[PDB]
Amino acid sequence: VHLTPEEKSAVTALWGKVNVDEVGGEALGRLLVVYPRTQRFFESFGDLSTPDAVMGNPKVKAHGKKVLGAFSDGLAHLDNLKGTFATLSELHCDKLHVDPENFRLLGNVLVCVLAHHFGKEFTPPVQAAYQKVVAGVANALAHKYH
Amino acid sequence: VHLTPEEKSAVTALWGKVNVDEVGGEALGRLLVVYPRTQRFFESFGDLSTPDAVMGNPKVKAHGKKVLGAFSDGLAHLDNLKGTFATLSELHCDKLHVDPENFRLLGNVLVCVLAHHFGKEFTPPVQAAYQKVVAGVANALAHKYH
Amino acid sequence: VLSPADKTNVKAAWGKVGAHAGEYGAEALERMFLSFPTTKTYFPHFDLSHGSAQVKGHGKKVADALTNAVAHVDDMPNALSALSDLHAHKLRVDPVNFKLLSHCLLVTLAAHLPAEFTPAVHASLDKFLASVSTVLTSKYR
Amino acid sequence: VLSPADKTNVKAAWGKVGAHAGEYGAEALERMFLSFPTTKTYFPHFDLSHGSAQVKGHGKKVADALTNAVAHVDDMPNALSALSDLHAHKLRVDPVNFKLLSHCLLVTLAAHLPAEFTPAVHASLDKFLASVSTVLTSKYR
Ligand code: HEM
Ligand code: HEM
Ligand code: HEM
Ligand code: HEM
Ligand SMILES: [Cl-]
Ligand SMILES: [Cl-]
Image 1 (tube, rainbow over the protein chains, first blue to last red):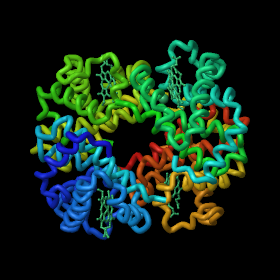
Image 2: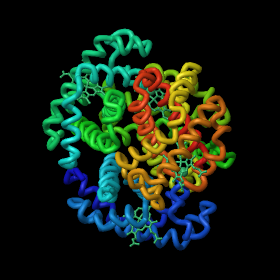
Image 3: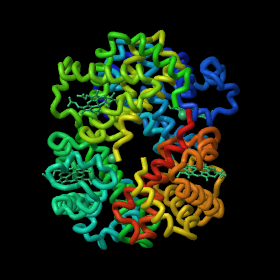
Image 4: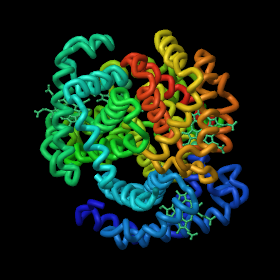
């Protein structure tokens, strides 16, 4: 990731305010609702039939928290996303069989979730820094696909 | 790019058999025909009203030879497309205002032209190596955009 | 296609935008210019500075057209034909860029309508923006 | 929107494919898997080695659907309804992969039908594969 120092300052500042448990569950639920196709990976999660069934699903919430947890660690190694996410990249490809395009969809949803949460504090330029981070993370997660 | 020695040799040896003149005129012409939207940058070339008019247009023919020329030269710096295309990347951005997405369209048209020409010889694995180069060239050409 | 439910969601969310449409259109453009700098290649003639009057003016125009597709949600292809002709014949904008704008438009709405920007409304607005984008790119070739 | 010339063009090109459609089907798949390895994520249960009978058989299936689609070029939505169902409700492949298969199919035709792969025919086949992709992804949400 090519983040100017001031971009990196802005990313870090805001991330300080996020409730990863909360945001993680919201981001993953919205993905499942906005792009139902993504539900292909979660048939063991139960009822994903309506927005409410998805958003309040205890399994979706727990998973979302796991995913954003891994993501937050990524935010402390912006310097080395590839190394950071290498075992996770292998797993998604080799065990989970997740098309990497899914990582970009989540990134965009997450950005909407941060806009939702921070309102006006999520400025055009703050969004531009997060767009870069999200693409960096999606890229690192797909680096080991073969 | 992240070309393997055996992938590097396949690219290299096929290119040795290419008539840049003919292949360049065909790739650029095919592009204006298949994706008519790309004509927005070649209004001054003349009559692009028909496939026959495009393929026949000499301004098109000569522009394609110039493009494939520069592409050709880049195959010599496969280990630093970015450094080879920096200036050309700046020009395309700051002077020509060409959306880098066009670079990807061309690359793919180019792959179809090579298959067209080489038939049998353009095997799945040879195609795979060229897809890597074309992507690499598109990425390098888009690198200095701001 | 847009379901009865989607249509209700879109009229409702867009209903709330109201008189802010223009301003939100301008903000969506600015967000796009900052986050996806390649979209700038289409506005070489614009002053893309923060608070550009051209951007303000362009935002209004985009906003008016979205407002028109909402008013004619059951006849979008005809309500937007003219705009679809312009885009196909003169602007000739690459299709991927429509997805970048749609995205920045959802960010803007989210940033301004926290209460209406529910998962369900989000899904509907996404399908809607996608449909508008599809109409505008329908006469390309 | 396929124009009458396109429909003609498509019918011709495909006409020549004839008894080899299944082989071109299988070759396109093989080029897809190699060029765009992320596409392999949808076939973890397949043997993706060169000349697998799974790939071969799958090529046939695909090629056959294309024939049926050319045959009902005027009624794709209808000729391919069961397929749009399958893709939208079971398979759920991300739309970008349709462009990667489409491309590998053009490449296959180009390599095998040199005389018929004129610029205008190339133009038509692309528009056609796009149309097919639209139909197959039309009931996703
Ligand atoms: C920010 C991007 C993502 C990160 C950092 C991430 C991280 C993780 C982690 C830490 C796990 C648990 C690993 C384990 O079981 O050992 C996991 C599992 C999983 N992820 Fe990802 N993930 C991401 C995106 C996605 C997306 C977008 C999808 C699908 C649309 C997905 C599908 C899965 C599935 C299906 C599992 C296994 C769940 C189960 O145990 O049943 N992931 N992910
Ligand atoms: C393979 C990728 C490409 C390469 C290596 C390339 C290279 C070149 C070169 C060497 C020039 C000569 C101009 C100069 O040095 O002053 C040029 C000009 C130009 N290119 Fe690119 N090009 C590529 C793709 C494209 C595409 C896809 C488009 C648009 C569809 C495009 C549009 C133009 C235009 C409009 C000019 C100016 C020519 C003129 O003024 O007559 N290029 N390019
Ligand atoms: C849903 C998405 C879009 C809508 C509703 C929309 C709507 C419009 C409208 C109403 C106009 C003004 C035409 C007039 O003067 O009457 C316009 C012009 C224009 N649009 Fe689109 N547009 C969309 C997407 C895009 C995208 C994604 C781009 C490029 C990134 C783009 C590039 C342009 C340009 C360059 C102009 C002309 C500006 C000028 O010369 O003042 N449009 N659009
Ligand atoms: C040109 C567009 C496409 C056509 C015409 C097409 C056609 C078909 C057909 C005819 C079948 C078999 C249905 C049956 O078993 O009765 C099928 C299944 C399948 N397709 Fe699609 N397909 C297309 C694009 C794609 C793409 C791009 C992908 C993913 C990269 C894909 C993934 C699959 C999978 C995973 C199956 C099931 C495989 C199995 O378990 O046998 N398809 N498709
Ligand atoms: Cl979907
Ligand atoms: Cl086009």
